[PDB]
Length: 142
Ligand SMILES: CCN(CC)Cc1ccc(CNC(=O)N2CCN(c3ncccn3)CC2)cc1
Image 1 (cartoon, rainbow, N blue to C red):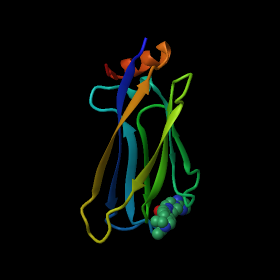
Image 2: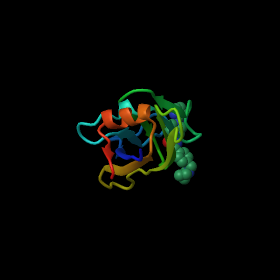
Image 3: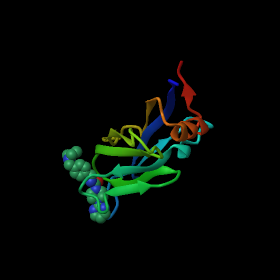
Image 4: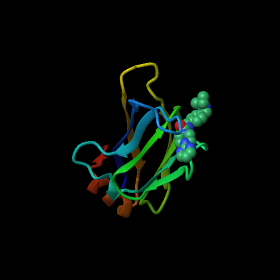
């Protein structure tokens, strides 16, 4: 039969000016994450999240295979971060790719506390992957 399942992801980041910079002239702490809304376990359908940091970072490929799906770092500039959310799906789609705007607060602006809400729509998932989406607190849309 036909069924379409929606699940929600929240991508987000925090950034703040360090009271004093680091030795390396890193002015900021930031943290970037992927999570579910309240009372959802996205781990049921998320295999892993890959955060692609700027080439300027060492081991810039950061993999979270279980919650929390987050990177914590200090740096001196914002950048565009590819974030891959890989699914426990045996068919397409196998993952989804976001271009995350990791910007910093500059010149004594308040800390950054940003959230990006994403709705994934899966058309006619397999029985297997449909279970996982539901277990995670996904919703049928018909
Ligand atoms: C906005 C586009 N442009 C600048 C306008 C290029 C650019 C963007 C971001 C960055 C961020 N880079 C950074 O903050 N990092 C921290 C970690 N670093 C490090 N270095 C040694 C050991 C460990 N970590 C490397 C430097 C840079 C350039």
